[PDB]
Amino acid sequence: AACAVDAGSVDQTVQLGQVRTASLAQEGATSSAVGFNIQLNDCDTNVASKAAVAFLGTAIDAGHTNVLALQSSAAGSATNVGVQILDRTGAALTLDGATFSSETTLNNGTNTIPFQARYFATGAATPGAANADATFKVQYQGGGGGGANVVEGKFHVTGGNVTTAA
Image 1 (cartoon, one colour):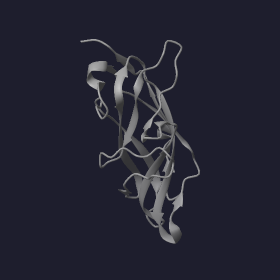
Image 2: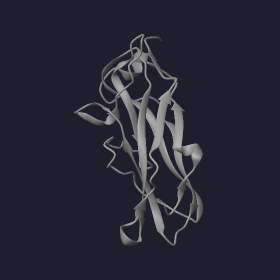
Image 3: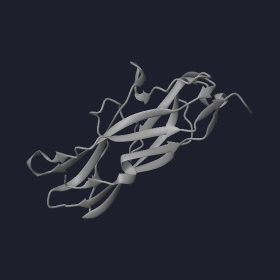
């Protein structure tokens, strides 16, 4: 409660564009990264000096706990690729709702915590839609153990497509 999550951040979406299978041909290949942020308003640094964000979603498998599984689709979604959420240090965050981003240091009032989303291949990707969803929670570093916003934010990736094309 040191801050409030901006309503525009509480339910938001990133679109990653179109990716070639040739660009996701082996584990660890990545698509281009697109930025987003979590905006906090009305921050009171009497209460908290720093904020961080954790993300929860279904991971693609046990060996890739920081890769978000894609939603199924009638036409067949891409396989061997999911979505990563990168914090300000470039690290992809484990999607267990308990692995927090590095901290953003706050001023009073409005602050933005920067992130990126990208596709990450776990193998040789195959073509199809590549949409994903996650939830997020904001935690503060402040007195008495800090605090947390009671809101559960929603993050979405839509408009994504993996194709086999030149």
